Length: 48
Length: 48
View 1 (cartoon, each protein chain N blue to C red):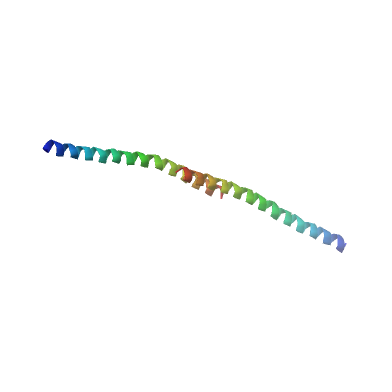
View 2: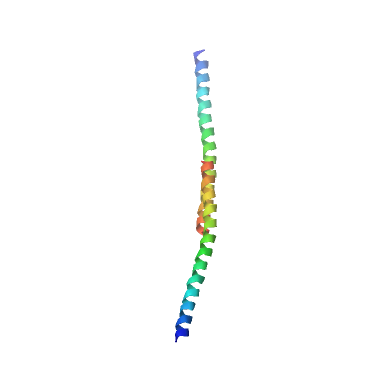
């Protein structure tokens, strides 16, 4: 039972960190679009 | 002589009114460039 409680905690804790690495890869891909949006903001002010 | 001078000043008004419309359609051309950049930012916001 003590191995099963330990194994259950490791499964929870690998899924909490597989998610955590997923959320940062998604944040790194999303910031690239906002950089290109902000380039069009600066390019608009050059057109203005 | 007064009639020919009236037609000269009339032409000078028409020159100013032409240059107002010429500067205004240069302004709208630059304002369509600015809107084309706004639309590209709205497309990048969509694919975001």
